[PDB]
Image (tube, rainbow, N blue to C red):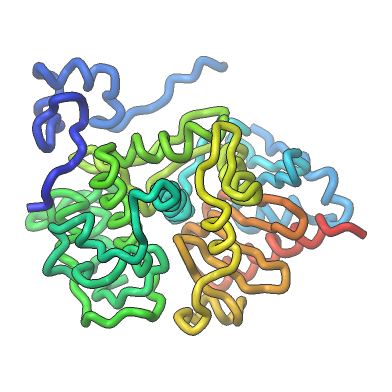
Length: 378
């Protein structure tokens, strides 16, 4: 048993509605206004072919930038310098206001929600996970602190299999018989040797954070992500997030939004944690993110080969490079990239044919770094 979870609507029974009950009362009142949460759905456009390239400013310094973006399967690219959009690119068929899957850039959004609750004094990172989610007793999350989840310094037996099972449990892939019912149940199945302190990138960590958020606030993670972050950004559009059969948002990977709106998250980070709608996280939280995590914990050569002094903290990758670059990162080429030096945010949303190869990362990081340097005063 995974304990109490936020009801899908006021008074809803646990787990209700399901794909088979949503037409029945009392479910149908909510379901009729939220059917996309139950059944896959397409937009029917209220608006009735060519790539949009407005690289302009930095185009002078980077002549072949558009070709480089094409080579890295770029769907949306946006550079925010201060409060100004100084460069934009969208591939043919992807509109400026279209939303794009964030993959694990979603994690950095989740960490931000956790940080907001730390700022409020409702989460103490030093406390064990089980202080907030007792039902994780007996799992690999029995013992580690919330901060160790945030920094992903927990040794976990997570086949990178657990990765497929995780997706099946959450509805990203077709369910197999014997699979856990939902994301919460999947998390309780996870085991490890009990060691901590070394970085191990594991998507399960972020979903535990979201579960903690739910227990602390009583809100569905879907709503917490809005209340503590999205609704304070003055975003152009809602974000979306995939949900599993209990309505639990896929915190570690399932958010989609526009490139411009994602940049508003970076802007908030470079503004000391303050957004147009109010403070999201504390100045201290932002400083700790920009400062990085323990370097010695970071033993992922896939990262340190490019960023030798890099680290990871609070759901952000920290390059530790001379620019102090930090980034949200998601597979197939998603970055929410911060360049504090120039007070700039770079959003790149892509669809590399492959999820995570040295080849694509090399090309992608080359672009992000070149664009960052192009923004330097000269």
